[PDB]
């Protein structure tokens, strides 16, 4: 379960349900679904389950992936969704 909290022209805000298993942190990945360009990564601690991703392009569809880190150090895919930025004003 993941919710998109806000979509702007250059940013996306998301919030995800906490991991069921023990978790030492999260990794959030943001990537253009179709059209090439760079992938953004940001990490959070286990008590942050929301994030705003900035520096995005307008009218681009992005995949947002959340990975959960367990104590062994493994990073496991938790939830992902596609979000499209709205156009510039």
Image: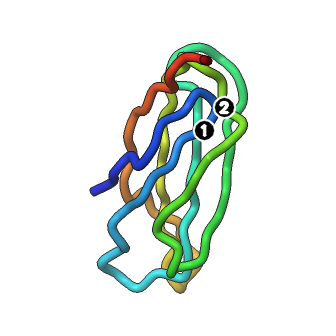
Residue in the foreground of this view, choosing between 4 and 36: 4
Q: Quadrant of residue 19?
A: bottom left
Q: Residues within 10 Å of mark 2 (few under 14, many from 20)?
A: some
Q: Residues within 10 Å of mark 1 (few under 14, many from 20)?
A: some
Residue 77 at what x, y percent from top left?
43, 57
Q: Quadrant of the N terminus?
A: bottom left
Residue 13 at what x, y percent from top left?
51, 49
The label shown at residue 71 is: none
Q: Quadrant of the C terminus?
A: top right
SS assignment at label 2: loop
The residue positioned 46% from the left and 81% from the top of the image is 23
Residue topped by disc 2:
56
Judge left or right: residue 35 versus residue 4. Answer: right
35 to 3, vertically: above or below: above
Residue 20 at what x, y percent from top left?
30, 78
The residue positioned 33% from the left and 67% from the top of the image is 17
Residue in the foreground of this view, choosing between 19 and 2: 2
61 to 43, vertically: above or below: above
11 to 49, vertically: above or below: above
Residue topped by disc 1:
11
Q: Quadrant of residue 42?
A: bottom right
The residue positioned 65% from the left and 17% from the top of the image is 36
78 to 22, vertically: above or below: above
């Amino acid at each position: 379960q993941m919710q998109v909290t806000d979509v702007q022209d250059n940013s996306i805000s998301v919030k995800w349900l906490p991991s069921s298993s023990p978790v030492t942190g999260y990794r959030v990945t943001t990537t253009p679904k179709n059209g090439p360009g760079p992938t953004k990564t940001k990490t959070a601690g286990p008590d942050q389950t929301e994030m705003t991703i900035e520096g995005l392009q307008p009218t681009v569809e992005y995949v947002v992936s959340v990975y959960a880190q367990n104590p062994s150090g493994e990073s496991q895919p938790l939830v992902q969704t596609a979000v499209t930025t709205i156009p510039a004003p």
